[PDB]
Length: 167
Ligand SMILES: CNCc1cc(-c2cc3c(N[C@H](c4ccc5c(c4)S(=O)(=O)CCC5)C(C)C)ncnc3[nH]2)co1
View: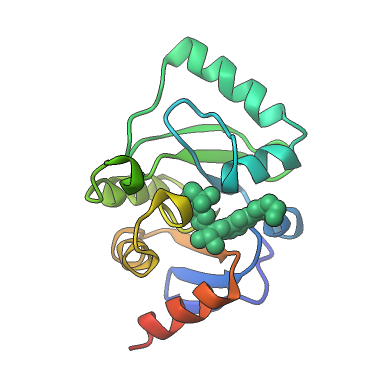
């Protein structure tokens, strides 16, 4: 958990302009959060990047989990191996508002982080999931009580988020 160069927003929420894959390699976190979908198909974006960094071992494990347990629910999660990126990967499904899912499920999605003491995570439901990233950060700060290090891989969005928080 050797997080470096983060800006502390509250006593338990930190943020950095960084690629979550590169952070996972530098930090060696106990838990890395994946921005998953309910069938754990890591086809692109954050999930595709984390799977590629494991040389597809995350996707094979994920397929075996789904075969035995069935899909997750939106707002839900599961704990699988972190492979070379962390001790564990917490796969969390935030709502995809571009696909009609309820933005209220973003609170349930962040609540899964409270089962782990320290996590490296992306900003849930942002990017092509369509939620307003300023709102996602607000839900994170209000919901997460354990220690969360957010990696946001876009300096333009990072600056807007820090300027929204410090208003
Ligand atoms: C350029 N080579 C591919 C690639 C991409 C990455 C890569 C992207 C990325 C990231 N993006 C942010 C984000 C946050 C959440 C969601 C998405 C996107 S999404 O994938 O569109 C849908 C699920 C939710 C974005 C708002 C700046 N944040 C952190 N670390 C990241 N790493 C490495 O390699």
